[PDB]
Length: 14
Image 1: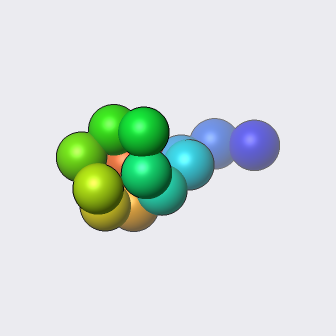
Image 2: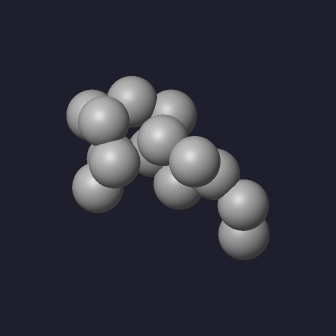
């Protein structure tokens, strides 16, 4: 549920 790639920095995100 934690860290969701994309919709962040085109990366692992989180």
